[PDB]
Amino acid sequence: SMQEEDTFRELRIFLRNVTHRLAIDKRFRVFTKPVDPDEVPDYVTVIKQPMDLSSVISKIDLHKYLTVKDYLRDIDLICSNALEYNPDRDPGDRLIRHRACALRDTAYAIIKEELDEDFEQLCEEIQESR
Ligand SMILES: Cc1cn([C@H]2CC[C@@H](CO)O2)c(=O)[nH]c1=O
């Protein structure tokens, strides 16, 4: 319905806002774009489902997220990808892992403070009805 479409439009507005706030954080710069095809040639062979904040934005705009839970799976993916691909004790790896965890934690904290639980429940019920 028109009302359901307004729901989803509101969802997308909320998700763009959260995603923008993550993307402008200097700590998260490395997650803002996909990893360069040639310049890290082994990435796409270790990491089967690359994800980054620009790809999140495109997915929002393509109406791929019908719930916050679905968005958060992609935030979780950005994180798990970073922990998987940079697993070493070396400071380079430890910095990106820290930053990945901080991205995840920040997104969850923003959502905990600002997402109405009844709004999410609605989204989930509309999705489950399709
Ligand atoms: C997403 C990601 C990026 N990098 C390096 C690749 C080159 C630079 C910018 O992509 O950061 C890296 O070493 N590990 C990663 O998990």
Image (cartoon, rainbow, N blue to C red):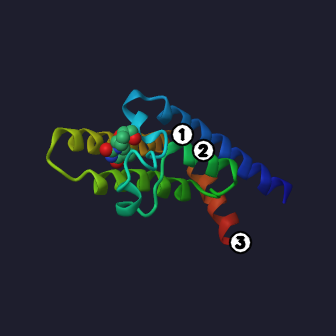
Q: Which residue lies furthest to the right in this view?
A: 2
Residue 56, percent from left and from top: 56, 48
Dot 3: element: loop
Residue 115 seen in the current view: no
Label placed on residue 84 = none
Dot 1: element: helix
What amino acid type should be assigned to the residue bearing mark 3?
Ser
Residue 3, percent from left and from top: 81, 54
Q: Which residue lies furthest to the left in this view?
A: 89
Residue appearing at x 60%, y 57% in the figure: 67
Nearer the observer, 69 or 81:
81
Structural distance between the alpha carbons of marks 3 and 2: 25 Å
Q: Mark 1 points at which residue?
A: 19
Q: Is residue 39 left or right of residue 59?
A: left
- Give the answer, above or below, for where 21 lies relative to 88: above
Q: Name the residue under label 2.
A: 57
Residue 120 seen in the current view: yes
- Give the answer, above or below, for where 82 lies relative to 28: below
Residue appearing at x 21%, y 42% in the figure: 94
Label placed on residue 129 = 3
Tag 2 or tag 1, which sits nearer the N-term? 1
Q: Sort mark 1 into few (<14), some (14-19) or many (20+) by Cα contacts within 10 Å.
A: many
Q: Nearer the viewer, mark 1 or mark 3?
A: 1
Q: Nearer the viewer, mark 1 or mark 2?
A: 2
Residue appearing at x 43%, y 41% in the figure: 31
Tag 2 or tag 3, which sits nearer the N-term? 2
What amino acid type should be assigned to the residue bearing mark 1?
Thr
Structural distance between the alpha carbons of marks 1 and 2: 7 Å
Quadrant including the N terminus: bottom right
Structural distance between the alpha carbons of marks 1 and 3: 27 Å
Ligand 1: give its quadrant. Answer: top left
Q: Nearer the viewer, mark 3 or mark 2?
A: 2
